[PDB]
Length: 442
Ligand SMILES: CC(C)CCC[C@@H](C)[C@H]1CC[C@H]2[C@@H]3CC=C4C[C@@H](O)CC[C@]4(C)[C@H]3CC[C@]12C
Ligand SMILES: CC(C)CCC[C@@H](C)[C@H]1CC[C@H]2[C@@H]3CC=C4C[C@@H](O)CC[C@]4(C)[C@H]3CC[C@]12C
Ligand SMILES: CC(C)CCC[C@@H](C)[C@H]1CC[C@H]2[C@@H]3CC=C4C[C@@H](O)CC[C@]4(C)[C@H]3CC[C@]12C
Ligand SMILES: OC[C@H]1O[C@H](O[C@H]2[C@H](O)[C@@H](O)[C@H](O)O[C@@H]2CO)[C@H](O)[C@@H](O)[C@@H]1O
Ligand SMILES: CC(C)NC[C@H](O)COc1cccc2[nH]c3ccccc3c12
Ligand SMILES: *C(=O)CCCCCCCCCCCCCCC
Image 1 (cartoon, rainbow, N blue to C red):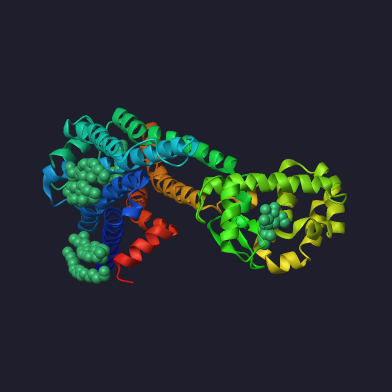
Image 2 (cartoon, rainbow, N blue to C red):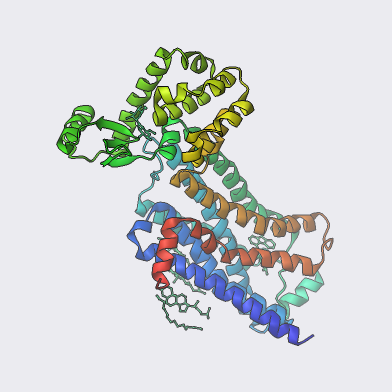
């Protein structure tokens, strides 16, 4: 009975420590490491502050209120505490929604992924998020617009040891729509469009960038030959200066061995052009290529990049099956090669691409697309943690008392606890993971 309290107390204490520790760690990492000082990370910091305030100002007193079974901090702080609670939750979803809109413009911009905002404009957007969240959280609570007019509530308001958030229905509806449902619907809609855009960037360049790798500096390939970019061969000569000469002549400037990503892409589109002409001159590949759709043609080119036309022309049975659209059987045969034996992962992705005729095997391979999934995970987690709570606010406007007080409280704590997850979700990033382990003396 009572020993349960201590044990429940220690648990809630660890929840508070978890929220404060992890969010402190996120703030410190972005504030300390110049590498992590990006526009997105400024909004993340804003998100981390809302969760930090939840962990220090909201969760500790909510815990105490439950364990003591009464409010001991008085009416002033009950109303203040209540205001911070609503503020932090409102600012969180408003920020998440700003991240979605920012990522949408970043990913659709011709200067792709750079936010259209400067660091200073981002601070103003953040400041404006906290002002708007305050205007929508503190005003109604401090102006007493939220309060119900029935006696049980009136008693609780006057009662210094009672801190139950009894509200009128109009507030229950209006506040929950404006603070939560509006920015949630926008976030979800806009960030689903971010994924569609991200998916739509997948193409042969990205495919070979994932499968072969883009190298900005001259390197020796497996045969010892000087190569650059996505396996672009410069010369078979052992003279480096001979490679550099060919590189400069190809790129159109003094490179000194180093090229930009966009120049690697220029060379790659030429190599692709060359591969296709070669395929169309090869009696055994031409019929196959001719019959394939655009995505499977990228598959074939991918293989020609890796093994040359001859190597690929030797897949006589697989080529015939591909020509007939017998995809699974083609895949059975292709999986039985020295190719799949040597580069299984790459082969897996190309064969699967021959199976589906979509780019699905290349989803979330690129660091930037992985980063977009991380953000999507932050958003989805927040949604799943708070949605039940906010559904019950509206359900109680329709028919009150349908769901027990203890269930409603538990759904609120699922919301609270969410303030501890984002720091763990950021361990998906290699940059945060590196940042953290430095900060924790590893
Ligand atoms: C009243 C309660 C909530 C206060 C407890 C706050 C705790 C979580 C604080 C107090 C001291 C803090 C640590 C002090 C120093 C460092 C080293 C730093 O480079 C990374 C963060 C880290 C490891 C801090 C993490 C958060 C920390 C442990
Ligand atoms: C509001 C009360 C009850 C709880 C304590 C509030 C604390 C957690 C808030 C108030 C002001 C906040 C700071 C405001 C500005 C910055 C600059 C930024 O580059 C790193 C975070 C940092 C340094 C914030 C850390 C958290 C902070 C100190
Ligand atoms: C009334 C009390 C309890 C509410 C707490 C409000 C605090 C936490 C709010 C008010 C203004 C907010 C800051 C406004 C602007 C920035 C700039 C950005 O680069 C980091 C976050 C940061 C620094 C915000 C963090 C949270 C913040 C400090
Ligand atoms: O065979 C056509 C392409 O070959 C090179 O790129 C290859 C490279 O030969 C090989 O060592 C490596 O395993 O794969 C890369 C591409 O994945 C050429 O220099 C390309 O320009 C040719 O199109
Ligand atoms: C213990 C209680 C006070 N906790 C409040 C929730 O954590 C967060 O609640 C909200 C956040 C944002 C907007 C909101 N509108 C509401 C209407 C009724 C109840 C809560 C909210 C609410
Ligand atoms: C390496 O970077 C990690 C070493 C940092 C250790 C710092 C020691 C912190 C002491 C914690 C005590 C504060 C507890 C406050 C409770 C209210």
